[PDB]
Length: 312
Length: 226
Length: 81
Ligand SMILES: *[C@@H]1O[C@H](CO)[C@@H](O)[C@H](O)[C@H]1NC(C)=O
Ligand SMILES: *[C@@H]1O[C@H](CO)[C@@H](O)[C@H](O)[C@H]1NC(C)=O
Ligand SMILES: *[C@@H]1O[C@H](CO)[C@@H](O)[C@H](O)[C@H]1NC(C)=O
Ligand SMILES: *[C@@H]1O[C@H](CO)[C@@H](O)[C@H](O)[C@H]1NC(C)=O
Ligand SMILES: *[C@@H]1O[C@H](CO)[C@@H](O)[C@H](O)[C@H]1NC(C)=O
Ligand SMILES: *[C@@H]1O[C@H](CO)[C@@H](O)[C@H](O)[C@H]1NC(C)=O
Image (cartoon, rainbow over all chains, first blue to last red; front, top):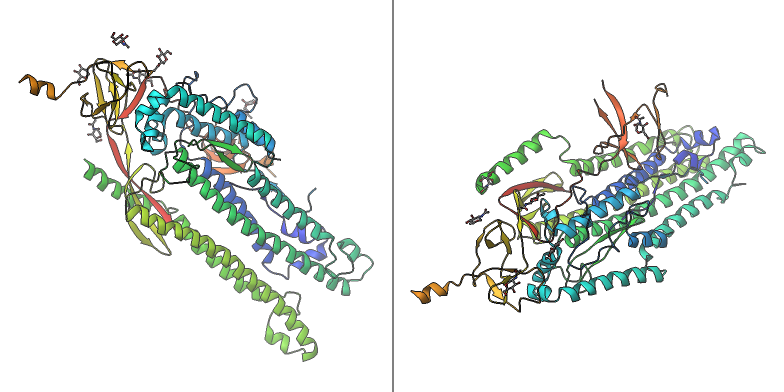
C-alpha cells in the first residue's frame, strides 16, 4: 500500500558542508528543486495512499463486548485487548514476519501503525455487525448468521443451506482461520510482496549511499580531499566532475523511485478497490476476492501493506 | 419525493462547486504540474551548467572556436540533461494520467452506460445512475446514489415454524414490532403479512437455531372456505 | 524560534509555536506520526493526536435487525483527469 517516505536532501547529498561545492551546484539551476519536489510528491501520495486504502469508513465502529456470533470465532482476527497494542493475533504474526544519514531522511507516516490497526478494527467490526450496509450508508445491525444467509443468497445458494448447516459452516470457518494463522506462522516467504517492497527500497537507498564513494573520474571521492591538496582552478573541475556524477546518481534514484511509486500507487489503488468491493460489500466479480464464490473479506494491516482474508 | 430530492441534490452540487474553490483539485493540480514543468524547462536555459555563460551567442562571440567548442558542449550536456529529465517526468505523468483516464473510461462504461453493483465505485451508497460532465482536461461524474436514512430496529428470526416446517423468506427478512411477525424487503421497511407466496418451506423446525413459532397465512385457505 | 514559550515535542520533530491539546479532533494540517496541527479558538495553533472519527458502537445482538424506513437520493461529484 505504501513504502518509506524518504526525502533525500538535495544539497546535503550532492555536496558536503563545503561552500564551494554548493556554489558550483548553483549553476545547475533547478535540477535540485525538481528532485526535492518529486520526492516530496512521492511522500505525500504515500500518505494519501494509506489514507485511501484504510479510511474507507467514517465512524470507528467497535465490536460488541460479548462475542456471540452464532458459532463463528473471530478471536483470531479481532483485536486482543490483553496485548499493549490493540492488534489481532494475525496482525501480530504479520508484523513479526515482516522485517547513518548522508543527507537522507525518512519521514514518519501520517497514520501510525496503531491508528491503521484502529481503522482495520473499525472496518472489521462494522463488517461483522452490519454487513455491507456500513459502507453503503449508515451502519445497520444484523445477526451474523443472518448476514451469512445474505451472502449465500448472494452466490445463488438459498438460505436454508446456511440455516441448516450453521454449525458445520461455523466450524469450517474457524478451522480455516486457524489454518491461515498456522500457514502464515510457518511459511517464511508468505509476506513476499511487502518484504520485496521493503528490500527494494533499502537496496535503492544503500546504492545511493554507496554512490558517494565513487570517484566518477575525479581524483578522489571526498570533497575535503579535493579541496585540500588541490588549488581552486582545477579543484573546480574536479568538483564539477564529482557533482555531475552524484547528480546523475540522484536523478537515477528519484526516477527509479518514481517508477516504483507509480507501481505502488497502482497496487494500492487495487487494494483500495479490493477493500471497497470485498469487505465493504460482497463481490460477484469472479476471481477478484479470492478463488471461488466470494462471501466476505477481512482487512488485516501489515507493515506498508494490507492483508485480506477472502472467505470464499 | 424522489424527484424533489434529486432536483435538490443537483442544485446543491451546483452550489458546492460554485462556492468551494478547491473542488476542481485534481484537474487544477494536473494543469499546474504541467505548467510548472514547462516553466522549469524554460528556466533551465538561464543556467550556466559550468560554462562561461548561458547564451550561445555570448559564447560564440568573445571566444574563438577551439574552446568555444568545449563551452558549447558543456552547455549542450546540461540542456540535454534538462530535456531528458523533463520528458521522463512527463512520461511518468502521462502514464499516471493514462491510468486515471482508463479509470474514467471504465467508470463511464459501468456507471453512466449502465448501473453498477460494484460497491463504492460509482459514488458512495447504492448506485442508481451517473452523468458525465466535461471539464477542462478531465471529466466530472454526478453519481446519483441511494442512501438509507431512518433506521428502525426490530426483532428478527432466521425462519418460522408454521406446522413443524421451517419457512424462510423468498426476498427479504423476518421482522416483528413486538407482537406480529412481518416479512420485509431488506433495504426498506415494507412490512407485510407472512404468506406462503413470500416464504418458501425448507426442512424441519429442530435443525434451525433461532427459529420462532408463528402462523403463516395461506392465501388459498379463504378461497377454499368461500 | 522566537516563540519559545511553548515548545512541543513529537515523533515528527520539535514543533515550536503550537501548544499541545489533550482533546482529539479531525486532521487539519498533517504533521506526522498521527499528529495534526490546527487553528482553533484567543486564537493559537494547536497540535493534537488525530481523532479517527466518532466512535459508534453498533447495537449488535442475536436477534436485532435495523431496517431503514426512507432514503436520501444523494448525488456526489467525482472528478477525474
Ligand atoms: C434499538 O436499539 C436501541 C439501542 O441502540 C435499543 O435501546 C432499542 O431497544 C432497540 N429497539 C428495539 C425495538 O429493541
Ligand atoms: C405491530 O404492527 C401491527 C400491524 O402494523 C399492529 O396490529 C400491532 O398493534 C403493532 N404492535 C406494536 C406493539 O407496535
Ligand atoms: C442470543 O443470546 C440469548 C442470550 O444471550 C439467547 O437466549 C438467544 O437464544 C440467542 N439467540 C439465538 C438465535 O439463539
Ligand atoms: C413451538 O411449538 C411447539 C409445539 O409443541 C413447541 O414444542 C415449541 O417449543 C415451540 N417453540 C417455541 C420457541 O416456543
Ligand atoms: C495533556 O495531558 C498531559 C498528561 O500527559 C497533561 O500535562 C495535560 O492534561 C495535557 N498537556 C498539556 C500540555 O496541556
Ligand atoms: C422520509 O423522508 C421524507 C422527506 O424527508 C418524508 O416523507 C419522511 O421524513 C420520511 N418518510 C416516511 C417516514 O415515510
